């Protein structure tokens, strides 16, 4: 997250960290035993870290749970990043409280203009590199359909949307991938891709979660 603020410890209670020995992706908790992330964050051997702020210190509210199975979206295309979404089941149910809670799936897609919260432990610099230990937050609007397509000609599909600032300076970045875009108390997006970070005219692109509700709910009822 570039141009963001320190969220505050456990104030994004649905944010999770995917650790394979180090944090590499973000995710969102959607129930006691299921996490949603970005398919391009898939790897064998994941541990899900819940209740994290500082990801290099044990502060007393963490739950570390191993993944029992991962399910990449059937139609994920890793060359164009369409359907960049995956599901992770946890080996045991998380214990939910005020500091570890799930976020709600949308019933309706969110419109352009809507202000959302984006969070993660990715790089905080637009040029060069500096990774924060504590979670960072950014409020950003969903951009029009049109604007998103003219910023990335030929690359935006019906399952992506852009959010951020076309003036630059505020954006998601490397290490934020798979993390939540929450708008009016629900999960509208997943940090998926962009062109550098916080460049003029190139806003971050997110997986449109509203298009996948049906698939998630069918998948978690049978697995």
Image (cartoon, rainbow, N blue to C red):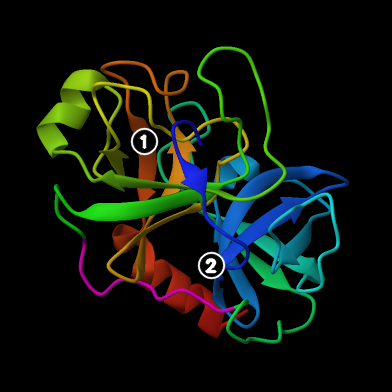
Eyeballing the image, is 221 above or below 25?
below
Instruction: Determine which quarter of the picture holds residue 94.
Output: bottom right
Instruction: Please count the marks in the image.
Output: 2
Q: Position of residue 155 (x, y in %)?
A: 30, 25
Q: Earlier in the sequence, mark 2 or mark 1?
A: 2
Q: Which residue occupies 55% across, 69% down? A: 14
Question: Which is more foreground, mark 2 or mark 1?
Answer: 2
Q: Nearer the viewer, residue 34 or 214?
A: 34
Q: What's the magenta bit mostly, secondary-structure-wise?
A: loop
Q: Is residue 153 visible?
A: no
Give yes or no for residue 107 being in the magenta stretch: yes
Residue 200 x, y percent position in the rendering: 30, 15
Nearer-the-camera pick, 73 or 110: 110
Q: Secondary structure at mark 1?
A: strand
The image quadrant of residue 33 is: bottom right
Query: Label 1, on which residue?
Result: 205
Tell me: 196 left or right of 210.
Answer: right
Query: On the rendered structure, is 16 left or right of 93?
Result: left
Residue 100 in the image: above or below residue 11 = below
Q: Give the residue at x 63% y 37%.
A: 175
Secondary structure under the numbered disc 2 in the rendered image: loop
- The residue that label 2 is drawn on is 11
Query: With respect to residue 139, does 105 lie above or below?
Result: below
Q: CA distance from mark 2 to mark 1?
A: 24 Å
Residue 160 falls inside the magenta stretch? no
Establish if 115 lies above or below 90.
Answer: above
Residue 34: x percent and y percent? Answer: 61, 73
| Residue 141 in view of the camera | yes
Q: Which residues are magenta?
A: 101-109
Q: Give the crowd class for mark 1: few <14, some 14-19, many >=20 residues within 10 Å.
A: many
Q: Are dots 2 and 1 in contact, CB under 8 Å? A: no
């Amino acid at each position: 997250i570039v141009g963001g603020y320190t969220c505050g410890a456990n104030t994004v209670p649905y944010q999770v960290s995917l650790n394979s020995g180090y944090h590499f992706c973000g995710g969102s908790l959607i129930d006691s035993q299921w996490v949603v992330s970005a398919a391009h964050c898939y790897k064998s051997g994941i541990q899900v870290r819940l209740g994290e702020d500082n990801i290099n210190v044990v502060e007393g509210n963490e739950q570390f749970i191993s993944a029992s199975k991962s399910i990449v979206h059937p139609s994920y295309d890793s060359n164009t990043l369409n359907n960049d979404i995956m599901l992770i089941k946890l080996k045991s149910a998380a214990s939910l409280d005020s500091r570890v809670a799930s976020i709600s799936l949308p019933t309706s897609c969110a419109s352009a203009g809507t202000q959302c919260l984006i969070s993660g432990w990715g790089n905080t610099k637009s040029s060069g590199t500096s990774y924060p230990d504590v979670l960072k937050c950014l409020k950003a609007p969903i951009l029009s359909d049109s604007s998103c397509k003219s910023a990335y000609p030929g690359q935006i599909t019906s399952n992506m949307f852009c959010a951020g600032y076309l003036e630059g300076g505020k954006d998601s970045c490397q290490g934020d991938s798979g993390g939540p875009v929450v708008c009016s108390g629900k999960l509208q997006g997943i940090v998926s891709w962009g062109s550098g970070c916080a460049q003029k005219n190139k806003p971050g692109v997110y997986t449109k979660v509203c298009n996948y509700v049906s698939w998630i709910k069918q998948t978690i009822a049978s697995n």
